[PDB]
Length: 421
Ligand SMILES: [Ca+2]
Image (tube, rainbow, N blue to C red; front, side, top):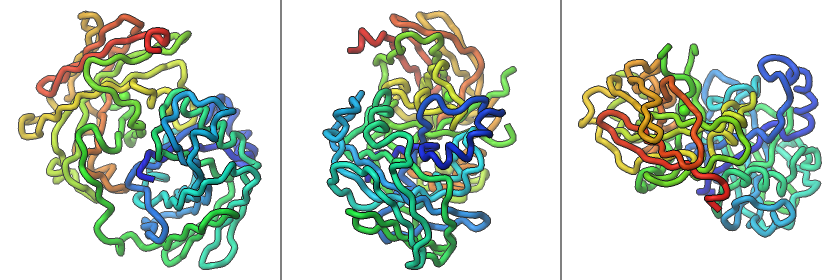
């Protein structure tokens, strides 16, 4: 509810069936070997009765579903014991633009303001064989059944928590079918299921929706963590952005685990921009008025776990403790130009990566304008701006230090699974 909302894509056999062909051809090559995850960040999350702001353009689809709600810290939950970690279930709505591609993360399609209605948590034993219904303006519009999902609730909790710890109050959306129904301004969309209070939301022209949902500020880091893919010219028509779940974050001089039996885990030094004022539809020219200042991240990746579904996916990029980030923020006024700073990485004192923000493809103002054009940025949100060339493998015992000129120096130590236990 106020927890992180994860969700699974491609979990309904109808979509798997529909996409079977596409999944054998470029750019997928092969069907998903593993669950395809996404996140509905805090700007999306609304309760019953709250409006879904409609972006004009622009075709929008309801996505009635149900979400498991975590009742206690879930790390490596065993399938057979899942119910003990689940407080209950809640009706939800993965509101989305069309699912035309599953290759790149679907941020414009799924992370718009108000795009995740979620209702009341109900303490049921399971949601087996549950028909989830959608009504529009009070008429029946759609129905589907959780028996047609590939992974059930227990399996989803076990699969995600295997690498990403969930906290009490976090949720998992169980998935949606291929076929969806379209909503438009003026519609009232209602989700219903036996055993739950109906969830209802009106769809309103976004130009008519008021101030934007705000949140209490908490010490950094606390906010949506956006991250760029390929953003250094060093050696894309539009930026590749994906989100990282907050349990990936860890502080200075901590440890990060390298999984057993993989070939390649690499650091990624990055300049991180932190938002200081709520921002929507901001021009490049005013973007910097919304920046609080800068910090540093080490955006690790396990290259082995990469797949071609919402790439780079959560099993690579939202690993528990695989994103060291400094807790200090350097105010923008202490940094004349963020587009002229050196980044470096050292492993055991050997310089392995060096670059400059002069090589950013997409500038800080471009990125702020680009994201705020389709979603609300709030104070404490962070934008990891990418990394220059110079990646390499790091192994247990290694000390990896990333540094951005004038912003900070961030230390981390790799350990084995055996050591971290
Ligand atoms: Ca990165």
